[PDB]
Amino acid sequence: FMNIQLISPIDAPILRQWAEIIHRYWPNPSQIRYGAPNVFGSANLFTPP
Amino acid sequence: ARAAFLFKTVGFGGLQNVPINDELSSHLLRAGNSPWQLTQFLDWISLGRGLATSALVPTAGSRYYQMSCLLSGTLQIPFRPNHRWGDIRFLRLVWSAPTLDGLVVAPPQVLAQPALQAQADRVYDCDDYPFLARDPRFKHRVYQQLSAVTLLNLTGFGPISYVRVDEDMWSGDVNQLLMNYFGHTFAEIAYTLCQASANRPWEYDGTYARMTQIVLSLFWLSYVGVIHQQNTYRTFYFQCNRRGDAAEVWILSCSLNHSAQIRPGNRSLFVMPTSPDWNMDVNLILSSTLTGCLCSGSQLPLIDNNSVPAVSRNIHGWTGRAGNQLHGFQVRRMVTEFCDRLRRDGVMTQAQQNQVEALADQTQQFKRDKLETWAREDDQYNQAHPNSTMFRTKPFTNAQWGRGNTGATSAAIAALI
Amino acid sequence: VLEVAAGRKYLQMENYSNDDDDPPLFAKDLSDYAKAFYSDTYEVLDRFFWTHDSSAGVLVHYDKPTNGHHYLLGTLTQMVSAPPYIINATDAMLLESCLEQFSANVR
């Protein structure tokens, strides 16, 4: 799974295609801003407030 | 906006070590092990409604000085070139966690090992410490109290405050926020502002910073006596019913009688008390604390080298070759200046001035006697114990009990308007 | 602060086969490898990154920038054309810039 070159293009073409699709089309994480910590403060621990 | 983060530690007042010991340190850390004790100090002074006192903390300035001494003596461990945080002890105390979160009793091995010998009048840069460099919010939160300590330790007199007058500061949001403090006192306003600053560091030219500068200017103008009920700064002033009292209370107020005329421009200067009786004046210490909280991201002007001792010269962010002069004053003489200015303005009479003078004289006598007695007790304790010498209040000299540049300071503050 | 997506720098043809002699592409041929933040002052950019994630890593050119002061933040993509190593985007751009500078120093 981590190294696609191990999957044979001839013996397992469908599996190689599926692995490539998984690597190049899985969703990408992102972030957004929320809250008003002026009054409520911030309770975030492992992330920026 | 500030670009360099430097601070100065306290200097020995004739002793051979930092004037603090285990008893004072334990009394300070009695209810919390965090060395950053601004909120604890605010709670202890109890809104400045009365004269706070204790066995080990005679005055509020005493606690302020002890906080400064504790921070100065403790911060020298992680600021060694090796930058190790938890391998050496200072007065049976060790840091917990590299992020400088609290002080705890030393482990048995460190207790057996010798302690650290601290030095006097050290100047340090916050960005040298790796963790402070890595985390901006942590550095900005700490630098407020570091700046307050520096403003107290810069000279041998009382703390330093910054006064600025500028008409362009006022705006709609500033007016809306300022109108909400119509009936509150200076101590309450300072409490709320300090808590807000602690929750969030302010930016360079924010609403909170501008309102803080406006409040400081209003308080100092009212204290001098340029602004009063019949001569207001945009219908705002500070009222004090009992001038010259031991614990003065100042209340924000509005009046539609008259508004003074303000010349356009931007002016500012630096004020400080010289007489030792500042230890029992909450308002001055709170003003200095507000200036320190402002200093986090504002980059105030430079202070002239000739107004500070040799060891405080050429600090990268604070002192400089050509800078503003420090104006020092005496409280008792400033009371007389206040009364005289009001009488010339025509809103006070001779009998009222005489009553205020008598009350001020009584207060000065009481404070002088108490301070001298406490100093003598400290001297005797230091004589008795040669291995745990300490000071409970910032040392002073007999010469500081006389009037200094009070007239010039009053004239400068009056000309500010 | 203006946020701009970073476009591709290389484009593959059909006969790219991850060969030993194929030129490396440093992951700059994928859809999104980095993201640029443009402003006017570095202190404003720094204040902006107080309340924004930066675990991936932030890179900067202090010399003449392409279109003005800007920071660059990498994504979670990977470079797999140089076995037996798997290299993420930030390290890939660092390596490319380092090699360019070394060639410039030589020539």
Image (cartoon, coloured by chain):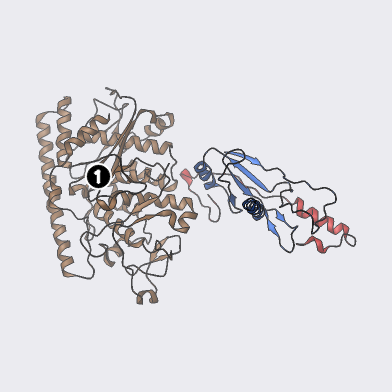
Chain colours: A red, B brown, C blue
Work out whether residue B29 or residue B162 is closer to the camera in this orientation and state it. B162
Q: Quadrant of the C terminus of chain B?
A: top left
Task: Check the image and report above or below for C69 versus B64.
Answer: above
- Residue annotated with mark 1: B306
What chain is tagged by disc 1? B
Residue type indicated by callout 1: Asn
Residue at far front of view: C107
Residue B263 image position (x, y, % from top left): 31, 24
User: Which quadrant is the N terminus of chain B positioned in?
Assistant: top left
Query: How many numbered discs?
Result: 1
Left or right? Give the position of B346 relative to A11.
left
Residue B42 in view (yes/no)? no
Please state which of residues B410 and C41 is positioned toward the viewer in this rendering.
C41
Can residue B369 be seen in the rendering of this structure? yes
> Is disc 1 surrounded by few (<14), some (14 to 19) or many (20+) residues within 10 Å?
some
Q: Is residue B159 left or right of residue B351?
A: right
- Outermost residue, right direction? A10
Pinpoint residue B136: horizontal percent, then vertical percent.
Answer: 48, 51
Q: Nearer the viewer, residue C85 or C3?
A: C85
Which of the 4 image quarters holds residue C55?
Answer: bottom right
x 56%, y 53%: residue: A47
Instruction: Give percent across and percent down for residue C30.
Output: 74, 48
Q: Is residue C52 left or right of residue B76?
A: right
What is the secondary structure assignment of the residue under circle 1?
helix
Displayed quadrant of residue B293 = top left
